[PDB]
Length: 249
Ligand code: HEM
Ligand SMILES: [K+]
Image (tube, rainbow, N blue to C red):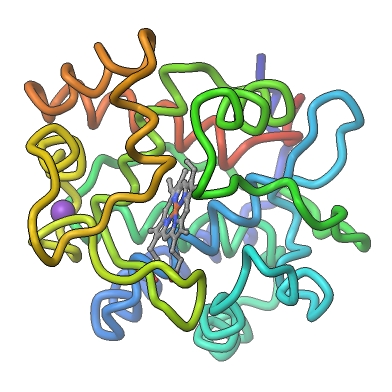
């Protein structure tokens, strides 16, 4: 149910140019996972009943960066500031969601469709909307479904973003990568989740909760068996996530 706003031809030119520059910058800096987390934490605060939070540029504000769920994201913000300054016409909201999309692409992931026009909003959402890694399926549904309005399929597919990157004991407290190849976007997150724990690889309780839920589990299996199906449903879910509250909810 989206109606995307009209942006000027100069705005579109800058999107295109910024997308190319983000590719090169993110690849060189090795920060795709962090950029994906930044985009996801920007968007994931959306509350459908109040139309508050969501991907509207507010993650740049010191007050939002201070949320405990956002430890380490000040690094991402600082890393993007010089590049953003080359594209003064773009909203931060658009810029961060573009950086998220590019992060997925440059690590070998699906091409997530991108539409411009998010406006930067003045007020961050209240803290505490982002998911708790120590919790389980009910919690995931409260956050992704009751607040964000995404589906059970979306929950599982988006969890697969853990296919890139790592936790850090100085940020969340958890430590290490989910996969043996943490700068490669693939279905390995689901193959590891299924195989049991392997030395040196991380599983949050929230990841584990996918295995014992009756709706999540068949999706895990599908994605572990079929990376193409993972990529389709991942791209669908990331697009929806990046558009929460934008161009209609
Ligand atoms: C499902 C609930 C989720 C929970 C509870 C969760 C929790 C976490 C935690 C605790 C970390 C570690 C942060 C650190 O210590 O550095 C992390 C990292 C990450 N998360 Fe999530 N996450 C979830 C969903 C997602 C989603 C939906 C995405 C993207 C689609 C995502 C992408 C990432 C990425 C890319 C990293 C790694 C960042 C890096 O390498 O620096 N997560 N997540
Ligand atoms: K991987």
